Amino acid sequence: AELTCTDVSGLTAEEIQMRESLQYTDHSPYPDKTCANCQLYVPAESPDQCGGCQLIKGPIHPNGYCTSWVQKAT
Ligand code: SF4
């Protein structure tokens, strides 16, 4: 199975609510906007693990997205 980053069981209800507010998804709807090209992403320690985010808590997929995506590209 591919890497999934939707296990929110270590988060508080309020932290989950923020993630939902921002429409976090593992599968970005946009070809050109993913967590991996967002300024707030923190890459994983292995490509076989989820990364993280400075803005929302919990596991974060590099192919994912939320509506607060902050462009890296100059
Ligand atoms: S701010 Fe949103 S798009 Fe950027 S890394 Fe975090 S979850 Fe992904």
Image: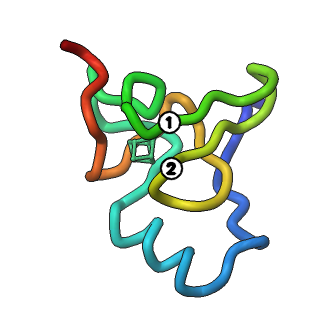
The picture places residue 22, in percent across and down from the top left corner, at 34, 62
Q: Which residue is mark 2?
A: 54
Q: Inspect the image, locate mark 2, and give the three-letter code of the amino acid beneath it.
A: Gln
Q: Determine whether the beta carbon of the residue marked 2 sits less than 8 angstroms from the nearest atom of ligand 1.
A: yes
Assign ligand 1 to one image quadrant.
top left
Q: In the rendered structure, find residue 41 and report the number of the disc placed on it.
A: 1
Q: Residue at x 69, y 42 (%)?
A: 4
Q: How many marks?
A: 2
Q: Determine whether the beta carbon of the residue marked 1 sits less than 8 angstroms from the nearest atom of ligand 1.
A: yes
Q: Secondary structure at mark 2?
A: loop
Badge 2 density bin: few <14, some 14–19, many ≥20, Cα 10 Å: few
Q: Quadrant of the N terminus?
A: top right
The picture places residue 15, in percent across and down from the top left corner, at 55, 76
Label pair 1/2, CB-CB below 8 angstroms: yes
Between 51 and 3, the one lying in front of the other is 51
Against 59, is 51 above or below?
above
Q: Secondary structure at mark 1?
A: strand
Badge 1 density bin: few <14, some 14–19, many ≥20, Cα 10 Å: many
Q: How is the image coloured?
A: rainbow
Give the alpha-carbon distance from disc 1 to disc 2, as whole Å: 7 Å
Q: Mark 1 vs mark 2: which is more N-terminal?
A: 1
Q: Residue at x 47, y 25 (%)?
A: 36
Q: Residue at x 43, y 70 (%)?
A: 20
Q: Residue at x 62, y 44 (%)?
A: 52
The picture places residue 39, in percent across and down from the top left corner, at 38, 32
Q: Is residue 31 visible?
A: no
Q: Quadrant of the C terminus?
A: top left
